[PDB]
Length: 140
Length: 140
Ligand SMILES: O[C@@H]1[C@H](O)[C@H](O)CO[C@H]1O
Ligand SMILES: O[C@@H]1[C@H](O)[C@H](O)CO[C@H]1O
Image (cartoon, rainbow over all chains, first blue to last red; front, side, top):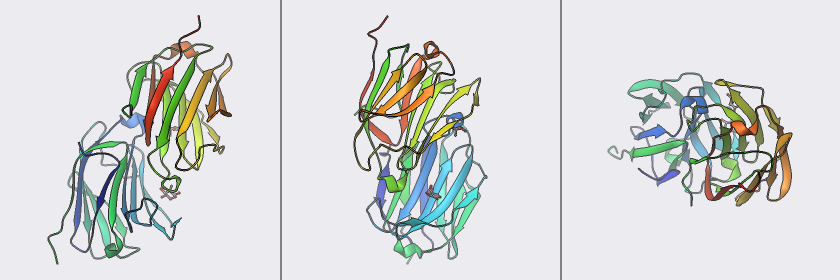
């Protein structure tokens, strides 16, 4: 297991993929959360280019935090995550948006509000255990 | 540090006190949570006689979960918790209600919906680290 909260310095651009494998720490009846934030600095209070928050079994909210203030969230009731199961998240940086795959299924997208090149850090936290975390760095 | 999620088998009655010392794992801008649940069985999906959930810097909700269904929550905007600080929670079982002290200050109360003798387990979880947990057992 990787430590949670998990923080890794990161850079992103079109073609980058962030892969996360983990499991919720509670049954869905107890409403565990999962949060992935792409930050503009290593500091936890820095701006967030992409905030992804799952309330397992209930909903997902996505937003940005710019100059310290939250912007307009996008709320989804799509819920591909399965109660009591390990999940694999694959986040792709496409030219126009982030695409979130859950267990290989396209499940959410979020249009860029800030260039992905502004990201310097990724944090994964809340009610999960993690077994894998990777940011790909294969493209120019 | 005690492991989080933290679970301890427990019994409560009038005069019992549950003491918890810990710290949030994130700054308040990031909205870390704290949850304390008094359960009717050791199973995490069991009923909850007293659910106490803090969204640090924002609000507190209290409720019960009976026969698998959440009842009517009580919402408070009282926020004695301080950003970036260790806190001490003291929960007293009074004849009529639970009284929650935060850093020695009376901060929330919740009238009994189910007898406290129905409790068999206490769970402390979400975005905190813990250094102390105690249930007192000094009274008849
Ligand atoms: O998760 C964030 C925070 O709760 C913020 O306070 C409002 O926007 C939501 O998307
Ligand atoms: O925290 C609980 C859960 O969110 C439930 O779904 C509704 O009641 C709230 O108090």
